[PDB]
Length: 227
Length: 221
Image 1: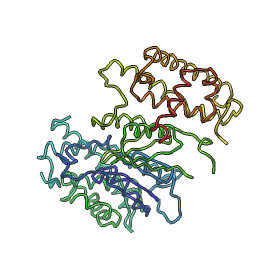
Image 2: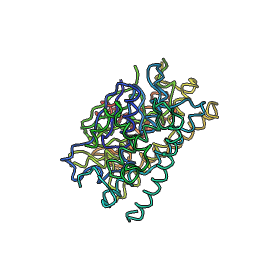
Image 3: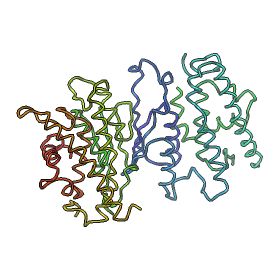
Image 4: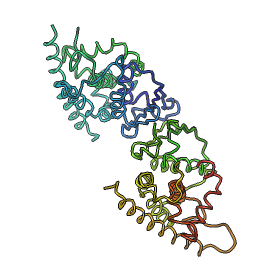
């Protein structure tokens, strides 16, 4: 009874879709994007996140924008069988989850993609077949490393608390996990994964990404996008 | 192909649909409104934003949808609802369109339901106080007087013979869409008699009676 209009390649669309799948909600999803053969240039050449906002229709209500869609889904579907991606607002765990979710959503993925195509010599194993100065790209990638180091320390805390492997903010899969997983998968697509993790660097994050890949929901909604 | 998600009762939805019909665009429209309490009991124009899906683009909000339809469908067969920006007629049409779109329809309808005494012939089977309703109704009368004077100018500029003019000229424009939908909603609420009719605002009265005869207006609304 749900209808979603989205673009497969759209970052925010991927987040919304993963949230739908995690919550075990039957949804009619329509990919408005046209085939590649009709576009003079692929999507990553022309991406505009501000112009590309998915739309959700649930009976009478019509909800634009991905974050609005996710919030509406989290507040509207309170059935006991449907999983919850967010802790109760009264709980002391909600601030942590919300902080990390905001952190991962603030990252400028469009800048990273743009920079990845303009400066392909900074990418490693970029999945593309293949403000504008390289110094700007260097800056934003170092900021990304700071955010990812914060994430690594949080994952280290989680690993300490575990003697049932835990996720980023706890045992339960949360919206912060959705944001982080989609973000890492997009970085992987761009080729910015090797500099940030792997080969003995950020091991907790590497294990996180691998575990995510094995997950049924994530694997059903994603993996086909990269290839 | 075009897809539209809207609410029949929604004011802005009505404007978007009238624009679609006036441009002769084939569109697939879905009424998402439910078949407990009526729509005029609960009103939030900000909550109910229509959405247009045109191939690969998704446009929320009615004004954005209308501007997009005008900028996109540039085929010579498809009529234009706005003059070109370079023209001296475009400022006039844009001013009047903004003037009509600025009106607080939500307030008028909420007050019509709240104060049934003020509606002469409603078609229903500090904002709450009556003074606010009277105040916004007087402002409405001022706006409609501006429209009335513009229509009087149209009458002066048109000869005895020939095609009768619309608000800003001879061609139907977006300002006409806004004005027609506004007048229709006022008639639904019962605020039409106060503003025109019975020798009151004759130019505006004739404008509305001419609107009702338009095939596109009668098909959509």
